[PDB]
Image 1 (cartoon, rainbow over the protein chains, first blue to last red):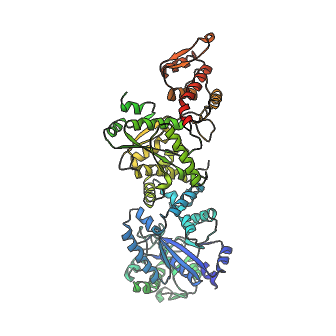
Image 2 (cartoon, helix red, strand yellow):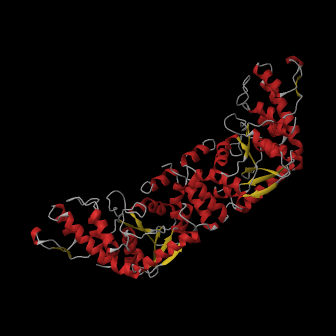
Image 3 (cartoon, rainbow over the protein chains, first blue to last red):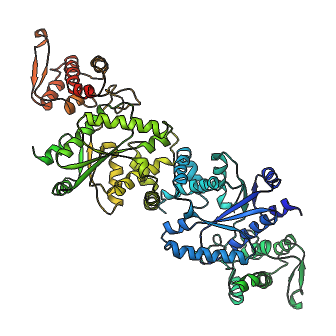
Length: 303
Length: 303
């Protein structure tokens, strides 16, 4: 599995593969991703940071943009409080093994130059196209909703990044960047993790997440409570966790009573067992809780 | 006719009269109005500048905001070219007798503070309300269309103005300001002059205007060509010109053949004559062309 394939692994989409291969051919390459500072860092974040780690291993300089301005505007606290959360986020990301440079949105997003270009971009972007780009991320829709995608695009341009990484929900905004900017950004899109209740995406504000520093008993309790319908793989958070975070061979342990220990050599194997209902939701949960704990331990320990 | 009535004269609307009376009671009061720099200054501008003149005569300090940034963003030339048009506009306004302070949009509209508040306002303004505010001013609608009204409002706030003056087309934007800002701006709205072709409003870009420095023969030709249907007063640019710019008693001159000279002591009088078709569109045009020339002469001479 070469550098390209290591980057591609577990992504939903790369726009475009041909363009990424060209990026790979150069010494100096950067990749960026934006996060709003968050009191809790969960599996949703972890999945994306693993992807950034794949990229640095391929020779990319990594830049994390912390959206402190977005938080501040949205009544979530003063800049200093938010910088404190942002700085905690840096520690977590480091604990995960990522070696990155960090930039806060407020450091450049109010620069005269940047703003002027937000207004330039807004004369070139239709409202319809702007709103369309926001459907996957967006009551009483505010004008801020159509400013947001333009700022994202403008940031891509201001920082001169080669590759932009984000979840699948960011894809139309990235498409917008590739049609509005002089230089086409290569886009790498990660799957959107389902929350533990199987309802929406995993979110810090929806209380449906596993945080990377949750205690073992908290992880076990949260897994036990998860949505995990037998034979159903679509929208199954426990299966997603198995696909994106666990290492194979995986051992699922069961009493002899019920078929004994089961050893699976790939997620695809694990998938067929579950579809046929040869693997019971309870034994899967058990195995996932325990493996997840061992995976997260060194992160939580460093914290 | 007292200071209030002199301000009210020939306005479409004052929001609100009670609030304007309170403004009048103070020593230090300011009134502002925004114009985009224009190669031609026409009767549309003149009407509004007459209103600013009424206000300074009432003790108001006048501020004219020149929208050089709006022009620049909209591909109309470099800032220096536009500042040159803006500076010409100042001379014209002075020639009309207005004694004002001038500020260009680019001097403050990209300030970190101002921009931050544009984004604050955008989180508080719905897209629907923003678009509604722009109907009277707005193919392929751009995101810039919903940013524009918020900037107008933000400018009202940044400059701390007491009274905002504009044409009736600005009214929903002004309403928006009065609901979004801590301090309610008194709003004075002037009628929107019909262009000479009777088609739209008078506009520099629609070639349907009389410029204040047009030559006498140009004025005569433009008046002669105007839309001026007998007995029709609504949407009649020649009648509007008579209402807003001419002095009474007005003498309309006609041969004895056709009823002789006619002397009217008010526009209302002039109106009834025209409705009953007692006054013929040609004699009205003739009288309006000639009076308009004498009115504009001292302005054109100073230029």
